[PDB]
Amino acid sequence: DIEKYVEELYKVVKKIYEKTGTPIKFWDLVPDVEPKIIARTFLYLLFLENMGRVEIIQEEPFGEILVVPM
Amino acid sequence: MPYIEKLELKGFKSYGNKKVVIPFSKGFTAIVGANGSGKSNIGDAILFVLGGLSAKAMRASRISDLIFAGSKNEPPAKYAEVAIYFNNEDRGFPIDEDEVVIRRRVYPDGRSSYWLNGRRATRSEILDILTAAMISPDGYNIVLQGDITKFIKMSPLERRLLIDDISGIAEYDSKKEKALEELKQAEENLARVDLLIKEVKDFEIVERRYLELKSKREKLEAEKESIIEFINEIEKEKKNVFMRTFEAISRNFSEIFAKLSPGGSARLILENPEDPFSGGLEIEAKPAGKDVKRIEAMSGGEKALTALAFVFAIQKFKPAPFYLFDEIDAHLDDANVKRVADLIKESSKESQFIVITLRDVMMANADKIIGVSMRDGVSKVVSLSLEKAMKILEEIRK
């Protein structure tokens, strides 16, 4: 039901990382300027991180969030 | 009203030996992540630091099982620790500090220690300070896993006592106890004077003593009568304050339930409207197109919407400092979760709300979102501001 959207987002993260080799800004991953879509992108990344497929990096609270695939 | 600024966890359940700080919105925070991330342990942490004694209520089998048991890269903790930081700028806490810190540690031997703003304190002292601030260790405003079922199975008497509390009639019970003490002394003095008059019944001596006793008796009788009137007045006022409170919350409950359950309706019921304190508080609800059912007979989503309508009916009359929800959406579809989240967001202007969820429709309405994920058997957090996010992305839309 949602598993395909989480996997889709993973493949996007991996493909972009294979091209830049640098951490991906969370902001660049959010496809619409709508609170539910911001929230859903964040959630799908947290799903991926709990499964060990990405790492979420944040230095300071409410600071820039970056994503690296594992 | 005071509100939670942050929560610090160290060695507590899935949170490891490096202190983890969880910041909160003054308004609506959502705590999100996968099931199994440790997001729900944050709810248990708040029950814990506010004095919870029941391991089961904190989703543990024994108190010592709250202590971080070690992970791939970490040893077990020597103790579990949680600290909660309240903003007190308006002195909701009777403490002359802009910040009130409560800290609890539990050790493998099962003992707990508490601190209040750095100084040691007993659990009783902590509960007293929380009571003074009208913060409940596990009151109606805390609805964690299993608490909707508890509210459904709750006795009508227990349900009324909740309204007794909100209404504030405890001050009337106090005044009554003191007037009964005065009445007691009056009666004792009357019986004493009555014995002395009986014995009295030399002429000048006995007449003098009889007149003085008859006069003391007359004062005592007037004093007795005025105390009895005062008690009667107190009892009327107590009933009045309770009924004013009940009728306003009852109205709230019907409106809110009709809003959460479109086409539905519901009522609070006093088992004895003539003397409310001799009976319980009952609930009947009629979902759209279904028969009238009574709350203990309700299942699934209807049951959760009813319990939530009751919580918000109270918070609209007398808002608590914060509300803490988890699993309230387990039997609600997206359409229903939307209605609850809108109600939460609208009420979050008057109370702090902390909702543990993975439902994006609930998430969407939050001021801040705390994402939780478990990395190598250890939970860690990432914090996001939705207002900030909206601004940053609107500006990128150029």
Image: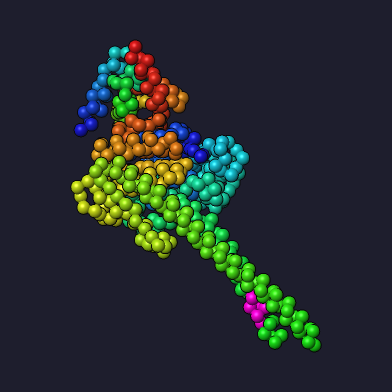
Answer whether residue B319 is visible to the viewer in this image: yes
Q: Is residue B389 magenta?
A: no
Query: Across the whole image, how many numbered discs are drawn on residues?
Result: 0
Q: Is residue B68 above or below residue B128?
A: above
Q: Residue at x 25, y 54 (%)?
A: B293
Q: Percent x, y for residue B125? A: 56, 50
**In this rendering, would B12 be left or right of B262?**
right
In the picture, which quadrant includes the C terminus of chain B?
Answer: top left
Q: Percent x, y for residue B351? A: 44, 39
Q: Is residue B192 magenta?
A: yes
Answer whether residue A70 is visible to the viewer in this image: no
Q: Is residue B380 above or below residue B181?
A: above
Residue B342 in which image quadrant: top left
**In this rendering, would B373 be left or right of A14?**
right
Q: Residue at x 46, y 52 (%)?
A: B167
Q: Residue at x 77, y 80 (%)?
A: B208
Residue A64 or A20: which is nearer the viewer?
A64
Q: Percent x, y for residue B76? A: 44, 41
Q: Which residues are magenta?
A: B189-195
Classified by dominant secondary structure, the portion drawn in magenta counts as: helix
